[PDB]
Amino acid sequence: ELXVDXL
Ligand SMILES: CCCCCCCCCCC[C@@H](O)CC=O
Image (cartoon, rainbow, N blue to C red; front, top):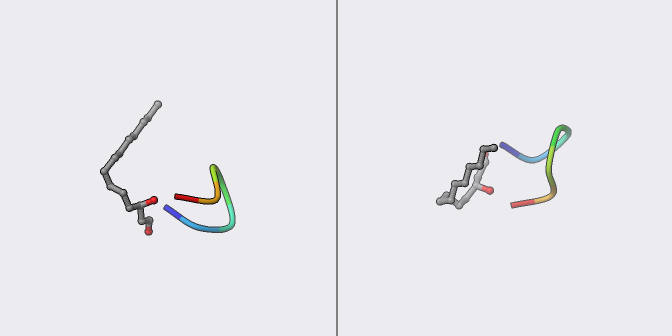
């Protein structure tokens, strides 16, 4: 969930 967490 890149944008949010990174990973
Ligand atoms: C608070 C939420 C934690 C979610 C942790 C998910 C770990 C497994 C997935 C990793 C890849 C993820 O970052 C790709 C997003 O699109």
